[PDB]
Amino acid sequence: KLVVSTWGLNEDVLKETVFEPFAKEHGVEIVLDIGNNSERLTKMKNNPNSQIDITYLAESFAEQGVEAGIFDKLDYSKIPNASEMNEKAKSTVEAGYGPAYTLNSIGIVVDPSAGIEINSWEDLWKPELKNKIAIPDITTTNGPAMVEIAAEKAGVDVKTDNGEAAFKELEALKPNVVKTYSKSSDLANMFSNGEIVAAVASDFAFGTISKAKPEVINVIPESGTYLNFNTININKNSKNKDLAYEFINYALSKEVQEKTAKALNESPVNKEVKLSEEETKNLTYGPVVDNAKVIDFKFVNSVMDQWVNNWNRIMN
Ligand SMILES: [Cl-]
Ligand SMILES: [Cl-]
Image 1 (cartoon, rainbow, N blue to C red):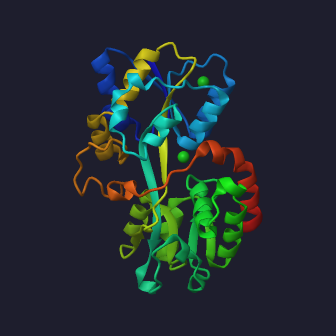
Image 2 (cartoon, protein in one colour):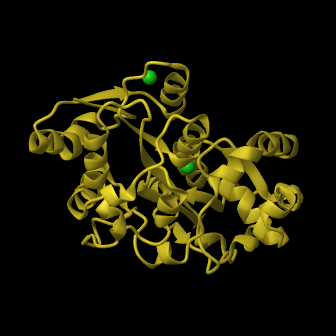
Image 3 (cartoon, rainbow, N blue to C red):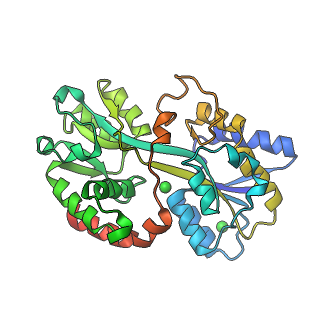
């Protein structure tokens, strides 16, 4: 029996595509413990007798579990498929705990009919964009990326000054920000109503906005996009670790990565995957990944309370 802590979104497809084949191949039963990142993480951190074997989380939350001492540092000699991960995703392998099994990216979604040229992240600060952009809130997946983007503009890495210069650049961006968001649905309507001309948004969000306003384009600055990952960890209290390792190795396999890309719109971390143009629609795939930047969540989580305070003080 393998107990899996996960979101369980599109549960039927998820079971059909990922868990059932594994269960049948290994002659075992899979049980899901579902909920959102925060509730699942909170429960396992406070439960002395957790029965969870493996845990799926966004990297930001996974790092909090690592810090809490809930997850095992992994023996990658038992996960040979990790050798097939792209160089950016391998940053999670180097970290030593659970590896990324999927990735996502951001871009600048732009309505080109406004005739305002936007090519780089720094262009978001142009005076012509007064009252015309939306950015992700600090509490969302891409909040940290937004602070790092501001750090690039300032020319001071957040590890040098804990982000103070980045926050001064965020103050400077204020006249152009219509709102900080949290919902993808929110952006589609803002573009449809002409409330914004540009938004820093995820690959998934570009797809949603495009359905409402097909003329929008997705600009990826030459300096590089920012990636975020979801990872799989083995719980330290697990009594089924050999099977847990087999499962992670399976989740990273070329076949499972291809199946989940197609069935669940999960961008692959396995560089050997064969996918068509229609299949990679709205996924993050290709050269974009090679030039991308990754975030150090060990560092970011250590300054998150400060960042949230600073962000709210500045943006409201
Ligand atoms: Cl638990
Ligand atoms: Cl994350």
